[PDB]
Image 1 (cartoon, rainbow, N blue to C red):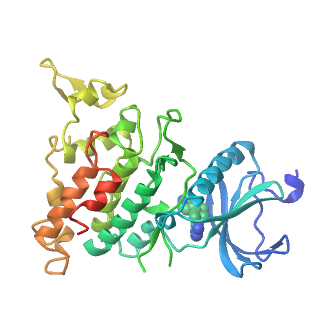
Image 2 (cartoon, rainbow, N blue to C red):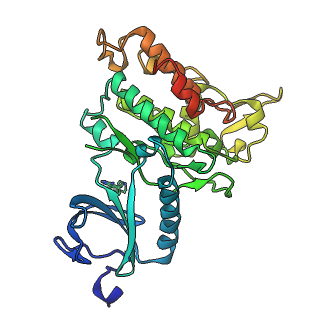
Image 3 (cartoon, rainbow, N blue to C red):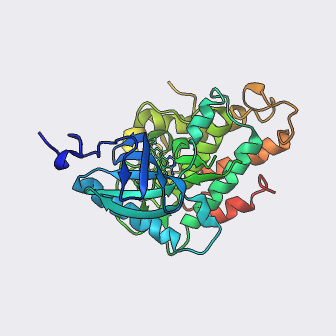
Length: 338
Ligand SMILES: C=C(c1ccc2c(c1)CC(C)(C)c1c(N)ncnc1-2)C1CCNCC1
């Protein structure tokens, strides 16, 4: 049984051969990753004389079409004249090779999850968190450009890469869409899933900001803020920290009744967790006790006043109301950055 004249396995993936030379241009070094879309190889480009990351899309129509959307979005972002652009991974070019769409990107380093592992899941300092936070708010401002309006739809530590410097770039626009395009109900990775998506509600660019808030707390503590085992557990861990969501949201939510019940007086409550709003971010961060674990007492940039400013920024990111949740332009104005 032969797939694609022998070039593919039985899973529509190109069979990666170490040292293969494509088109008298690319020298394939190695496989550096597998995903649903296909694979990523490290390769040397002879024309440009540099190492690149080549995303090899599966030879299967469902995956080709998804990647054509991904290419269209990266090419749109590329056409834009800003320095904000460079917080997104740069698509250099694309080609077909043996019936596979290949995307050529700049070679980046490891992701923010890898970083956290290398902290033994104790987190990075508030200062590094702040630099990560600023770049990420800047990236989200760029995506919020009226002509782009890209919702990422899957922000998480493993989709933010180090270049090598604490320079970082967003990757994986493979779940992404533009505002005004229709609804998909099961989106975002579970720990980073906005309450509107949990509630089956219409969403916009604010879902990215919600993920961002979850991310930043994680980068500093070492662990996920809301580590849900499923959707019910997820909404419940949100409610522990942030309380019961506004009545105007729940009165309207196609999936309100999955997590909440309307009590006889018309108020909402959950259907054993800490009571709504009782696991305070204030404590998770250790605002007054020398940061998380107490591991940052007296370190510069880690005063009680610094932590309060950080706590304030996150809670604006974790606002239940997507209309009022902090937006990228103003997140950059916040005193955490000043
Ligand atoms: C196959 C994956 C993957 C591996 C490496 C990279 C990417 C994705 C993204 C890009 C292509 C941007 C890139 C880059 N530019 N430089 C270096 N490595 C990468 C995985 C990661 C974990 N989740 C499943 C998919």
